[PDB]
Length: 134
Image (cartoon, rainbow, N blue to C red; front, side, top):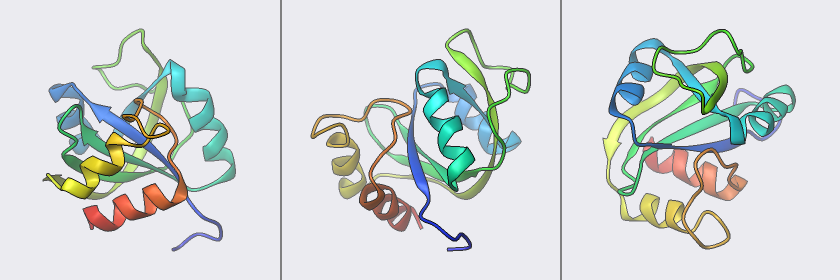
């Protein structure tokens, strides 16, 4: 890649139409409090990608590089008390793609059960998902 080290990858389960549509236009995402510390820690040590999939269906909506650390005062309008702060993103792919393999990876991402929003995935999973979304 353009990077020295492997990237780290996080899943964003999208259940808010305004949010995802706005993020594709403004290149900012609101990071949930449960997952923010891990994401911020990761951003300090590695290139970080967010992989965005639709909740339940697991259609792939795109993937983006995270290009700023968590900022408690730079948040999109649609954020709420569930969020810690905002991060800027750089979209690599934007799409609306159903793939059985994408869905299977997301369905088994948490020790063989369905992905938890904001979780870090394994390298094999993130790299495969970005390959499938390219």
